[PDB]
Amino acid sequence: DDDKAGLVEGQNYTVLANPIPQQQAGKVEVLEFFGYFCPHCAHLEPVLSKHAKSFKDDMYLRTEHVVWQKEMLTLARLAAAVDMAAADSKDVANSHIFDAMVNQKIKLQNPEVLKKWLGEQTAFDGKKVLAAYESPESQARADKMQELTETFQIDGTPTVIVGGKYKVEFADWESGMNTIDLLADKVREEQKA
């Protein structure tokens, strides 16, 4: 409970009033709330994904699209479809979705626009994702993303949470990875007790 350099509440991280349940019980969840419309998310993605590879075995990256209004539900549904249809190639799919919105200003929250765009995608399996998008399960997942956004009051993106309990305060994406590692150890020490 003593503080240490790189792990100061209010400076390097913040404590959630209410913890977010992890998907997996035994390990340390790194949870990123993001938006495909989010420039900072687009940039943190490569770094965070890269770092996640060197993650110890009891450590994984979970991502969830925020839903701050009705129109945004479509984007969370796309995110879910990516999770469902392209879990193994999520990096590349997201790379192009991010680029489409942040750089090309494509209105992917509009379903007609999204559906047609997905059908034209070669870099990733646009058609497989479109199929997941059209199944109800993608929307079920999106409804859950909206509930997470609201229940835990995620009002900004990116928002990275470690162990369901600690919000990372990012100076820069690289020095944030350090806080993630520190927090992960803090959380492991906690699980032991």
Image: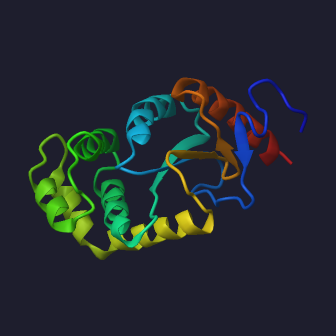
Q: Which quadrant of the figure has residue 85?
A: bottom left
Q: Nearer the viewer, residue 162 or 154?
A: 154
**Within the image, what quadrant is residue 116 found in?**
bottom left
Residue located at (29% from left, 50% from top): 86
List x then y, in percent, for residue 109: 27, 61
Query: Is residue 14 positioned above or below 170 on the image?
Result: below
Foreground of the two, 74 or 55? 74
In the rendered image, residue 172, in percent from the top left (x then y), is placed at 55, 27
Residue 50 located left or right of residue 161: left
Query: Observer-nearest residue: 163 or 152?
Result: 152
Tell me the quarter of the image containing the N terminus. top right
Viewed as shown, does residue 44 lie left or right of 91? right
Q: Residue at x 66, y 31 (%)?
A: 179
Outermost residue on the front side: it is 105
Residue ID at (17%, 52%):
126
Q: Position of residue 105 (x, y in %)?
A: 23, 47
Residue located at (26% from left, 40% from top): 99
